[PDB]
Length: 202
Length: 149
Ligand SMILES: [Zn+2]
Ligand SMILES: [Zn+2]
Ligand SMILES: [Zn+2]
Image: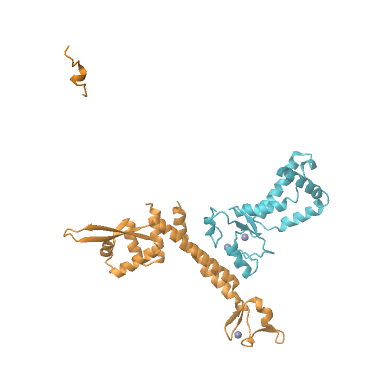
């Protein structure tokens, strides 16, 4: 197991999940497979506390589980749950997860491009510049709202365009460690007497 | 493909080589994810440099070096001038003499202002547009077709 896989798992779990998930995953990182009862005793978590965490790691399929059965010293049946990290599904799911963020970020960027510019202070409704000919009233010489029969403003449209870019842009700047980690992880038996001599008396 | 990408959207470039970077007069790497924002405000202004663009002025390019992008764009423009053929000069120095200043102009234009460059280009255009540019256009297009063939 390359250290890059271990580091990738540690970075993503610590980056987007609680320390409980990281500590639980660290055990599966330190040892490829560990029993649920062992992880329970090591973490000292409650059953539902650990199981819910494990269910999350199961939800994103970062970990896999197999059941092993054996007979105890007294003869009673025993069934232990062995959990293990699946770097293959982990890297696949994180790539999907990040590709989904990219689609969401692209959607947020496209929204930042489509956001309405004109707006009404009465109903707090923002109108796209396409409506400008409908909003502008020549009797008044200015933009007005049909629902509020009141002035419609436009100059405030710079604020949403600038502000959204600040939040969206920083996403790519901070994800750089995961992207780098991803780029780094894309890869005797003699004849008898009767056959030896003449048995005829002569 | 190997480069990180646009100063903002440096993520799809690693995924596939089908997506290509776009060059602009500002010599800035841009693409749809960033370009869509440039139309909602300013309508053709470089994000970091602020320089305005007369139109979209976007062209497909697959060079990671923005200096080469500019230099090629500049080269392609400057080749319309000073490109008179060798028979025009009897002396060996002349064959590459103007090429020196031309290469200086092309190179310097990648960093310095085009004020003196455009003035010199215009001052020579007033003379070269009469005959040599008319003649070299034919010879250049002819030899270009010979290079294609
Ligand atoms: Zn209104
Ligand atoms: Zn620039
Ligand atoms: Zn950009």
